Amino acid sequence: MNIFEMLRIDEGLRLKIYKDTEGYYTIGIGHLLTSLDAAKSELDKAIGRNTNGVITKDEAEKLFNQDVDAAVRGILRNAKLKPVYDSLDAVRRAALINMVFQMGETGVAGFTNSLRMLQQKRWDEAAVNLAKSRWYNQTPNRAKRVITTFRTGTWDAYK
Ligand SMILES: [Cl-]
Ligand SMILES: [Cl-]
Image 1 (cartoon, helix red, strand yellow):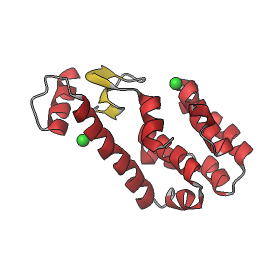
Image 2 (cartoon, helix red, strand yellow; image 1 turned 30 degrees about the horizontal axis):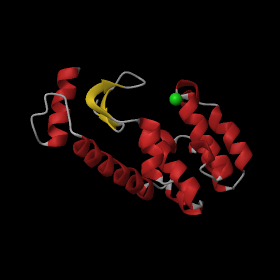
Image 3 (tube, rainbow, N blue to C red; image 1 turned 45 degrees about the vertical axis):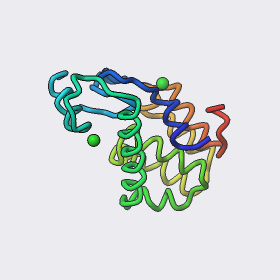
Image 4 (cartoon, rainbow, N blue to C red; image 1 turned 180 degrees about the vertical axis):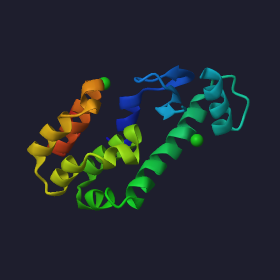
């Protein structure tokens, strides 16, 4: 199991524009675009071609690669995230990247209390704290998966 496999399971694959769990235009593997026209535009600009709203698997994967790379770099550039990331083992690092991919560096950065818990390796507590969020309430199955990953340090929730 790895980050790519982990996110591909959390986000699914869609070759046709679509609306996200919160109604935003998205495509491929959780590639957030945002108006459909505005979204079509963004999409065209992301792909460099006239897409008419549809992409190939290859195209979705290209975006996905760019996006995982971007999440990692953001983490590493972030003064609040980097120290947490540095203190973690490989599996849990994957869990942090997943959250970033989904909510953005900023969104994750604001889980201040949880972060401190993670940094201090208080597993059970951080799992409980992480659960007290809109994120958990809005996409509970996904959230439960990431949280179990932080709590156990294993890939059991994905297997
Ligand atoms: Cl892009
Ligand atoms: Cl979910």
